[PDB]
């Protein structure tokens, strides 16, 4: 009904399987687990980086000759970003390039932009052209990147060329609205809204629907929560995991994060006497799939609580050990009292991101 596009996901389960194969870790995990079960055991650090799922799609096009690109979706950035044919860096060499001279619809803007991050540095310029996905279209100001430094095992090894922002945060000062806001402005869609539908039975797929609430994706009502930040898909919620709880937490919806995160303190209380096993030397917390002590996780707002049963926050690891599962929950300290809801939450809740109203909505996904 509304324009929907599918995107691929490389998730942390996949990357963990790759590590396991790379380093021949299966039997090690299996024997450590067997040790825990006997139970002959007990007797630090992961990176927000490592928790990133890659959400990518290849059908967005720039300019009227439809220059093809592979984009990953970024839920915090408001900009779209693409390697310039002028790009200086060796990173750019294997990538698809935007060549403004080849489009009749390009309009020069040339305002320079610069991103400086821990992970790396991006320099470029604003350029204006048609940006299409693929039902939808709008002349749009995006960053043409002229230099890319860092980001640098991922970028080269990825087939990703650029970033397509589904967030709020614009690097310009030119008040370039998000691509989805721009769509609504030029009347390509009725509302500056999109939704994420992550099908529960295909962890390598998600769907983005733009400009409308597609009823086929969900059962029951949609509950909306007000953003608690001008520029973040982030909401106030009391979080309860068993008897471990934190009031007025900050909870970011980020379907590009591969897991549920919790502060490290909070997690330690959670996992104590939950009979969950931390495999030595690996960032891998493991438990039996039927673990009868694992609680329903609760995210409570004044008028709705969002929950996740063990079934939705564990990942079977049966290709390692029968009835083994891993915890899809990672202890990580961001700002005080900040939690993120990533892929596992969104496998249960169809989610709606409403730029016009500064709301996020949730409904019980269908199994499609």
Image (tube, grey):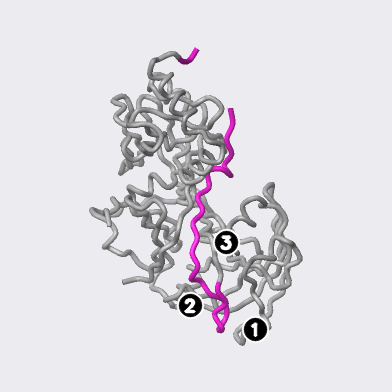
| Most foreground residue, 54 or 342 | 54
| Residue topped by disc 2 | 137
Asked if residue 96 shows in the view, the reply is yes
| Most foreground residue, 153 or 53 | 153
| Residue topped by disc 1 | 102
Left or right: where 30 falls relative to 89: left
Q: Which image quadrant is residue 366 in?
A: bottom left
Span of residues in magenta: 41-68
Q: CA distance from mark 3 to mark 1?
A: 21 Å
- Residue at the far right: name it: 88
**Does 324 appear above or below 122?**
above
| Residue topped by disc 3 | 160
Q: Earlier in the sequence, mark 3 or mark 2?
A: 2
Does the magenta-highlighted stretch encompass residue 53?
yes
Mark in front: 3 vs 2: 3
**Does 210 appear above or below 117?**
below
Residue at image point 38% right, 45% down:
345
Left or right: where 88 falls relative to 181: right
Asked if residue 314 shows in the view, the reply is no
Q: Quadrant of the N terminus?
A: bottom left
Question: Which secondary structure lies at badge 1?
Answer: helix
Task: Using a 10 Å C-alpha cutoff, classify the residue at mark 2 as few (fewer than 14 neighbours), some (14 to 19) or many (20 or more).
Answer: many
Does the magenta-highlighted stretch encompass residue 163?
no
Left or right: where 30 falls relative to 100: left
**Does 151 appear above or below 291?**
below
Task: Using a 10 Å C-alpha cutoff, classify the residue at mark 1 as few (fewer than 14 neighbours), some (14 to 19) or many (20 or more).
Answer: few
Residue at image point 54% right, 54% down:
76
Tell me whether the residue at label 3 lies in contact with that at label 1, contact meaning CB atoms closer than 8 angstroms: no
Where does the image place residue 230, in percent across and percent down from the top left? 52, 53
Question: Which secondary structure lies at badge 3?
Answer: loop
Where does the image place residue 60, in percent across and percent down from the top left? 51, 71
Q: CA distance from mark 3 to mark 2?
A: 21 Å
């Amino acid at each position: 009904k509304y324009s929907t596009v599918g995107f691929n996901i490389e998730n942390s389960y996949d990357r963990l399987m790759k590590t396991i194969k790379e380093h021949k870790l299966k039997n090690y995990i299996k024997e450590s687990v067997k040790l825990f079960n006997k139970g002959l055991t007990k007797k630090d650090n992961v990176e927000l980086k490592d928790l990133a799922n890659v959400l990518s799609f290849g059908e967005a096009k720039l300019g009227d000759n439809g220059q093809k690109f592979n984009f990953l979706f970024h839920t915090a950035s408001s900009n779209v970003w693409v390697p310039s044919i002028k790009c200086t860096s060796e990173s750019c060499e294997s990538k698809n390039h935007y060549d403004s001279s080849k489009s009749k619809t390009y309009e020069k803007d040339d305002t320079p932009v610069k991103l400086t991050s821990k992970a790396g540095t991006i320099s470029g310029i604003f350029s204006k052209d048609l940006v299409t996905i693929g039902k939808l279209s709008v002349p749009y100001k995006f960053i043409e990147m002229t230099e890319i430094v860092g980001f640098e095992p991922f970028y080269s090894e990825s087939d990703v060329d650029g970033v397509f922002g589904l967030g709020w945060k614009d690097l310009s000062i030119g008040s370039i609205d998000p691509y989805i806001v721009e769509l609504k402005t030029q009347n390509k869609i009725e509302q500056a809204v999109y939704s994420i539908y992550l099908p529960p039975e295909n962890k390598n797929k998600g769907y983005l629907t733009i400009g409308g609430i597609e009823e086929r994706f969900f059962d029951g009502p949609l509950n909306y929560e007000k953003l608690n930040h001008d520029l973040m898909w982030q909401v106030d919620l009391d979080v309860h995991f068993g008897n471990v709880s934190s009031k007025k937490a900050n909870v970011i919806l980020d379907s590009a994060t591969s897991v549920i995160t919790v502060p490290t303190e909070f997690f330690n209380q959670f996992v104590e006497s939950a009979s969950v096993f931390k495999v030595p030397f690996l960032s891998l917390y493991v438990t039996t799939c039927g673990n009868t002590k694992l609680p329903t996780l609760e995210y409570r707002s004044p008028n709705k609580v969002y929950t996740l049963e063990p079934k939705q926050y564990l990942e079977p690891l049966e290709n390692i050990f029968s009835a083994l599962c891993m915890l899809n929950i990672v202890p990580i300290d961001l700002e005080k009292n900040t939690f993120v809801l990533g892929d596992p939450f969104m496998r249960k809740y169809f989610t709606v991101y409403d730029y016009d109203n500064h709301t996020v909505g949730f409904a019980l996904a269908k199994n499609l």
